[PDB]
């Protein structure tokens, strides 16, 4: 893989291929039949015009499209059954977004099976991803606080039912045109419960991976919180720590070193500094819960939606 500056997730888990990294007919038909039962029946192509590809992903492509009867725009994510890194994770794309209506979760309208593709029709977030903004601009604390608040509200809800997102980074936060903020990328979730306390699968984007996850130890909803820390580093410093190193070299460093600090603490409020110390804590048991964090003084800094508007490409 290694070049560095790589944004693309990495998906394995709980086996030998996952150790290696310390330095079909029957199954398909069964899996397809199962999905078929889980999704909404029908074919969206019967009600949707104008499919144009607008985005590429680890698990598939995204197109915009037109509700024929209404003119309304929708986004459609299309995922191949044969082209998945861990086929079973596709259940997430259907189940999660459905089970979690919330002001900070992207809305899902419907899901269908089309050929050997899973298709999810979801609301179109006209604002774009956070990543764009972070890589081409400097958010002030008011705007940063507004972002974390939204993300944290969503995470509190997922973690309440022991759902781990496993892919928290700017590429996963989307925006409406009027400065509202939604979490978006539920492809790689896992769940914990009273009888499955932790998980051991190696899933995430290298630079954003919690260090206990890298150390192949059993993890929990805590990993998301470390990743959020890293996302804060993006919003401030523009890219994650060790971004320029190759993913594998970066991980090694994350496992071994002390939690990363911001480049320049001269201009950052102690309120924000203190916040981030609650996120990037190596020992998970010490690291803060989204529940707790929602009460942190820093988030009272959070500006309204209107204060996010100027950050978006249309207005730069
Ligand atoms: N509802 C939406 N509105 C606008 N843009 C979207 C929407 N959904 C996705 N996109 C854009 O298209 C891309 C689609 O990839 P997405 O992040 O949805 O999942 P993925 O990388 O395929 O897999 P995973 O969900 O497992 O991380 C994103 O990078 C995002 O910028
Ligand atoms: Mg994504």
Image: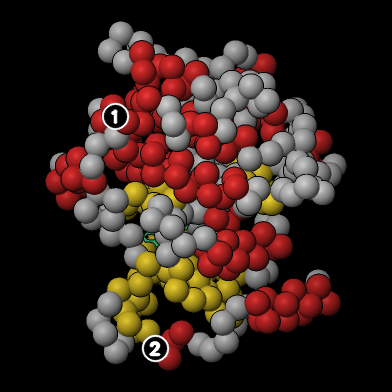
Contact (CB < 8 A) between labels 1 and 2? no
Q: Is residue 295 left or right of residue 287?
A: left
Q: Is residue 286 left or right of residue 133?
A: right
The percent coordinates of residue 47 (x first, y second) are: 39, 88
The percent coordinates of residue 248 (x first, y second) are: 64, 30
Quadrant placement of the N terminus: top right
Q: Residues within 10 Å of mark 2 (few under 14, many from 20)?
A: few
Asked if the beta carbon under badge 1 is closer than 8 A to the nearest atom of ligand 1, the reply is no
Direction top: furthest residue? 266
Residue behind mark 2: 47
Q: Tell which of 69 and 99 is nearer to you.
A: 99
213 shown above or below 74? above
| Mark sitting earlier along the chain (1/2) | 2
Q: Tell which of 247 and 220 is nearer to you.
A: 220
Q: Is mark 2 on a helix, strand or loop?
A: loop
38 shown above or below 272? below
| Front of the two marks 1 and 2 | 1
Quarter of the view holding residue 219: top right
Quarter of the view holding residue 280: top right
Q: In this view, does 112 lie to the left or right of 284?
A: left
Residue behind mark 1: 301
The percent coordinates of residue 157 (x first, y second) are: 53, 49
Q: Tell which of 208 and 100 is nearer to you.
A: 100
Q: Is mark 1 on a helix, strand or loop?
A: helix
Image mark for residue 123: none
């Amino acid at each position: 893989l290694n070049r560095g500056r790589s944004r693309q997730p990495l998906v394995l888990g709980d086996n030998c291929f996952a150790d290696l990294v310390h330095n079909q007919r029957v199954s398909h038909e069964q899996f397809r039949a199962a999905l078929q039962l889980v999704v909404d029946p029908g074919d969206p192509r019967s009600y949707l015009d104008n499919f144009i590809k607008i985005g590429e992903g680890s698990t598939g492509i995204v197109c915009i499209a037109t509700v024929r009867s209404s003119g309304k725009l929708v986004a459609v994510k299309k995922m191949d059954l044969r082209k998945q890194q861990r086929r079973e994770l596709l259940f997430n794309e259907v189940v999660i977004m459905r089970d979690y209506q919330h002001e900070n979760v992207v809305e899902m309208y419907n899901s269908y099976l089309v050929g050997d593709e899973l298709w999810v029709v979801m609301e179109f977030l006209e604002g774009g991803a956070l990543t764009d903004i972070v890589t081409h601009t400097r958010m002030n604390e008011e705007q940063i606080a507004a972002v974390c608040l939204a993300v944290l509200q969503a995470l509190s809800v997922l973690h309440a039912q022991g759902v781990i997102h496993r892919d928290i980074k700017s590429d996963s936060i989307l925006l409406t045109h009027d400065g509202r903020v939604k979490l978006s990328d539920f492809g790689f979730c896992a769940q914990v419960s009273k009888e499955v306390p932790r998980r051991k699968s190696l899933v995430g984007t290298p630079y954003w991976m919690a260090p206990e996850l890298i150390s192949r130890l059993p993890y929990g909803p805590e990993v998301d919180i470390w990743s959020l820390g890293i996302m804060v580093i993006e919003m401030v410093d523009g890219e994650p720590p060790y971004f320029n190193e190759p993913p594998l070299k970066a991980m090694k460093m994350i496992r071994d070193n002390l939690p990363p600090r911001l480049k320049n603490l001269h201009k950052v409020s102690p309120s924000l500094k203190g916040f981030l110390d609650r996120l990037l804590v190596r020992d998970p048991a010490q690291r803060a819960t989204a529940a707790e964090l929602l009460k942190h003084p820093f988030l009272a800094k959070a500006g309204p939606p209107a204060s996010i508007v100027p950050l978006m490409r249309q207005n730069r």
